[PDB]
Amino acid sequence: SLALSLTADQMVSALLDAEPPILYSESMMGLLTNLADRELVHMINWAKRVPGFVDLTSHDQVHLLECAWLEILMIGLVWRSMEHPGKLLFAPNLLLDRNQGMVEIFDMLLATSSRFRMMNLQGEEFVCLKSIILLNSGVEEKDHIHRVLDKITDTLIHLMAKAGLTLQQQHQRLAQLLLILSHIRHMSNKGMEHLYSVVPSYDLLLEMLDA
Amino acid sequence: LALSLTADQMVSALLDAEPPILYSEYDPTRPFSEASMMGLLTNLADRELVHMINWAKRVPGFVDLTSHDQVHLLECAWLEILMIGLVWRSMEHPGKLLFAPNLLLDRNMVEIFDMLLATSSRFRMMNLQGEEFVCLKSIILLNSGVYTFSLEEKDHIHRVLDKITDTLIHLMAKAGLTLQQQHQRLAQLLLILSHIRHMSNKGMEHKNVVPSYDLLLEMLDA
Image 1: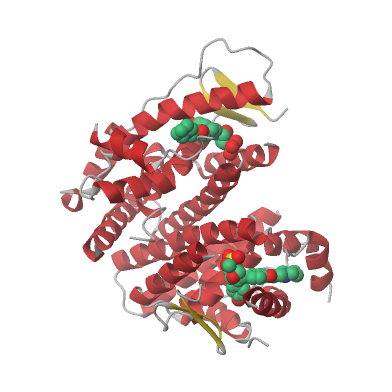
Image 2: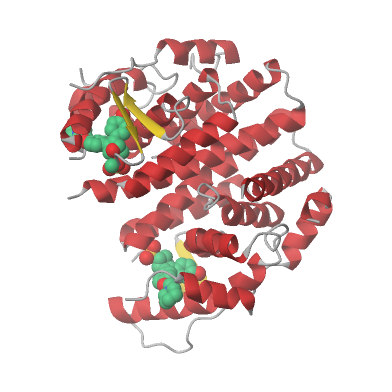
């Protein structure tokens, strides 16, 4: 695979160019649903640019997206709201605070954003985490996925070492970031059930990917 | 002082703090019904929650927290902790879940069963060690509920979490793994915790469900 031959800088470079744009919004449910739908179209294009992803069968690509799509939207939102304490930046024209807040998810999203802030999470680290979520949430195929995940781990470590972190600080920060993903999974699952009152089907995601 | 222990002392403390393996109610009516099954699992979990409290209070740094914060962490992690314990017990039993030594069940509800099976085979594949297991379980306890905690208490937990990370890496280096393999294995282990969170959430949704704040507090003060 070409993904397995990528260096850390190349992995970072690839993920950075694959970044979807920050979309604008056009009731709260309507605006967010409209935003989420348009975001999903970009997520498909982004996923197909994640190194090692298209090497998977179309069936495996769908399953990964079906499991991780809300986590990816959420970590995006959290990343966007990082420099706006006490507020969620769904869109540049849709900045919501706690009072406008569902409130349980809101607080957890706020807590994740504040966590990214105190860790001063970098954009290079962020795109690494986002692709990790894609490949891990729904995980020869499983073997290949785990190899790519090792690459992203090596990529994360290289970024930290280049930033001047000691070997100890490197495994600690690596641990801190990956444990945040556990909280992201939790927010996603709670969001899913609160959503059932709307979700991308297997067939829908397969059709979008085939474009 | 938890933050003063060495890596070997951390492992030693975690191993000594391990809860015992419990049996489900002896001689239940077989085969099972959906009710009688859940009746046995509920009974087993309720008896396990008691020993988990004892284990929790022996986890380095946990008793340093206020009772309120201790309850919160347990309120968030208790099902995760029961599940990773289940997955650990089931490692040497391919295609089976070992809820109890007298309660070994195969696939033949089913979605969670499959998820637990996959995780167990994942542990078996990685050759997960006991010293690594108790570290992961301690991480779950301290991490699952940390994300809504005063600032000195949240900072303290992260230091203990950093300590267990050091302990994991120390175990891997001591075993002979290269620095790259150490990073990779550490990552693979913590990513599984995300799956465990997922299984816990699916299980939760599946009159007395939550352990209740008051019960957990009472068991803690005792």
